[PDB]
Image 1 (cartoon, rainbow, N blue to C red):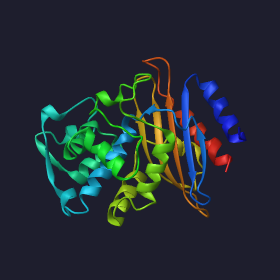
Image 2: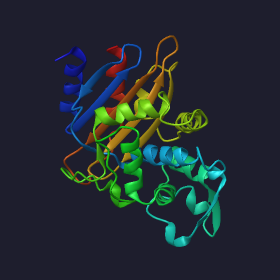
Image 3: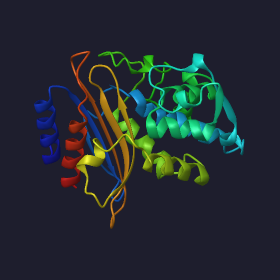
Length: 262
């Protein structure tokens, strides 16, 4: 048990919940894992796979991001901060992807899932890029029920870190697509209290957060320190009480521990 793992375990013990961490240090290809093969509910971190899948479609359908998609009243779900602005109108697939990734818009995620043929089409893209662990089973909002022990809509911290690496640093997408995905993740508006809050302020970050029932609080990030090779960090957290409060501080603290542990 490494020093870093002792500090993560102590964090977890202080928190009352269950913590999952994976780091990939791309310089050494070194990894640090904490509960690294346990399943965790993904909640909105799954939007990264869905958006990536659509980007993969756009490598042959070249104007696909420009395609208008009607937003109907009946499309609206539980959390639609961008899409309620465009009801009885349209949004493009790039707009929908941005809304999903940068504001965690759930109606936008559902449009991405639809474009891929259902939750199975998202899982199909994960299997196509090598990830045998991720599984998306539901649409929003039910994918975030985060019920303890439920395998639906889960991944592991190990798998998700490998996937995020392959998507943002490793050629799973076309270079136009990848740089889109990076732009989007760097532009996330919902991550300031999560991984970003635990990292040196000179480091550039792209991230996607997630949140659900059972106080589920997640973040996945690609990290570029100035001076050294980038890192991928995945932090998942979930709690025993169905109505538990969010704990983005845990994710920040987990990130600080990994950053100080390099």
